[PDB]
Image 1 (tube, rainbow, N blue to C red):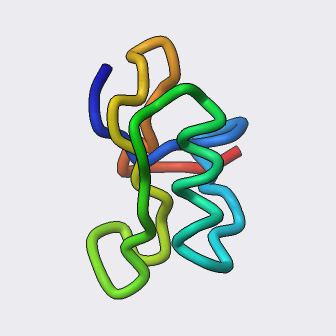
Image 2 (cartoon, helix red, strand yellow):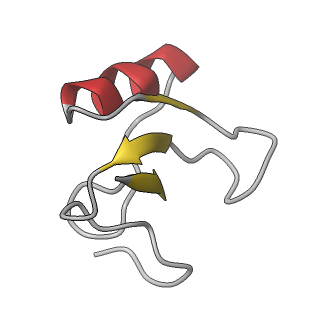
Image 3 (spheres, rainbow, N blue to C red):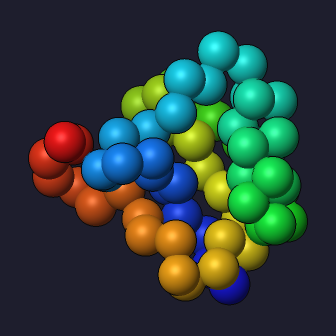
Length: 64
């Protein structure tokens, strides 16, 4: 369990139209909750909380 910019496949963030979308996705993954730094770090990412370490993080590099 950690915080993470959650990714899909690979290192690419999901289509956070609304903050809720990301909290939803995040909780679907069995995490605590999430939210979307639009005007914040990474800039339009999906932050998830208590994401189990099994699921990787959006590293500050490529997206495939």
